[PDB]
Image (cartoon, coloured by chain):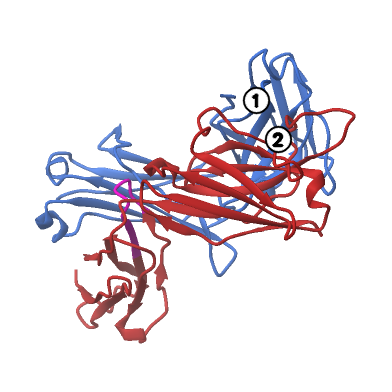
Chain colours: A blue, B red
Amino acid sequence: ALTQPASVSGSPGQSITISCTGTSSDVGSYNLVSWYQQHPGKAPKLMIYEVSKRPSGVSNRFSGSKSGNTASLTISGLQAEDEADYYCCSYAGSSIILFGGGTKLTVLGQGAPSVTLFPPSSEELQANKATLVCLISDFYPGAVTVAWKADSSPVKAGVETTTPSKQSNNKYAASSYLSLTPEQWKSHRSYSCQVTHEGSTVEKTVAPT
Amino acid sequence: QVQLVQSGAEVKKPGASVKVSCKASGYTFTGYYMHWVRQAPGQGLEWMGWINPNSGGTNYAQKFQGRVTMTRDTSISTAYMELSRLRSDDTAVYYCATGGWIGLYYDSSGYPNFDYWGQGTLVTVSGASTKGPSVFPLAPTAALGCLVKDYFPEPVTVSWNSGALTSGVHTFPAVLQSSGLYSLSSVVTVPSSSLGTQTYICNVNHKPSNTKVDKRVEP
């Protein structure tokens, strides 16, 4: 489908860029590319339609353009409320519509996460199963990235991470569950949860001991 | 105030079929397309195809043709989406979004101009069977909690000391594993001067399986 960067990272004040690169059977054919904004647990919001057009309510710091097969959304007036996921969408002929891969904007600067990592309980190991619990809380805005480590390697083997949920203080929380056999627990020296929120990364680590 | 209001979340066995509604109010229902878009828990958006609220003319992506049937009742101004032969990966949030207007000057469906959306209806297809959770202790100012693991369906309730405290208590949203089973954790923050001098207990309830379980946390 349409391909856009996995992550964009700006800092309050202004200027930024998100690219939706497509084929010639689109973008470099139609003036039919829309840009949508999605906050955690909410419906996407039309920020840009038909390449360069703004709906009603959408601030003039959002804009778009195109060059051949490259579509470009730019936010010039960056702001912590702008931290969200951004989707490219376009009409690729034959009466079908395609979406982007998803670009995750992050605003370097100001609510840091409250990571708390729990190791597999003494009992669960006796149930022939093992689970690592990375608990994240009290971070704003609601966009965070979670990466797991086995000693010093990216695991990714069944990580199950939750979409951030609004709390009673208008802040967010998330949870990451690493599932593995106890055999791959007594083996490796350590396991780490890396929580990246806005450039700043908080890392917790535990070990079999 | 144009707005779309959909139905509220259904859990279906794999191999079944689900039908989602979308009530449009604020405009002439028969003058704008309605496209249905879905997204997986953690993944991105996916176009499922459009409908013409007047002629009921439909078109879908070539990977939905056969399973998806999009209809509409114009009397009550609502659109319907039916997904058949539900598979595991068909667990997603299903949105209804208005499109471009209908006119004679130009345009087939085409236009990805979804100005107004709906609150999304989440369908959950899983190896559906009711099961009580397994509760594990999470031992260590310090924090301690309970791992409520492998249950179905939503929801479960977690308390502490039968409600004697609510301070530092923070019950997390559940996660849906690839085995169609849920799991969450409930953590609480307490002084490191209270260890061995105060009993901390998590009380969990999963009514659908009805499983009340008290579990204690010690270092």
Query: As displayed, is residue B70 above or below residue A52?
Result: below
Asked where in the image residue B7 lies, by quadrant, the reply is bottom right
Query: As displayed, is residue A161 above or below residue B136?
Result: above
Q: Give amino acid for label 1.
A: Cys
Disc 2 + disc 1, Cβ < 8 Å: yes
Residue range in magenta is B176-185
- Mark-to-mark CA distance, 2 and 1: 9 Å
Relative side of B18 to B130, left or right: right
Task: Locate residue A189, reporting x and y percent.
Answer: 18, 40
Relative side of B117 to B213, left or right: right
Residue at image x 29%, y 37%?
A: A157
Q: Secondary structure at mark 1?
A: strand
Q: What residue would you read off at disc 2?
A: A35
Asked where in the image residue A153 lies, by quadrant, the reply is top left
Query: As displayed, is residue B115 above or below residue A10?
Result: below
Pick the front one: A120 or A26: A26
Mark 2 nearby-residue class (10 Å; few <14, some 14–19, many ≥20)? many
Relative side of A32 to A159, left or right: right
Task: Locate residue A105, reporting x and y percent.
Answer: 61, 39
Q: Secondary structure at mark 2?
A: strand
The circle on residue A20 is 1
Task: Locate residue A63, reporting x and y percent.
Answer: 79, 33
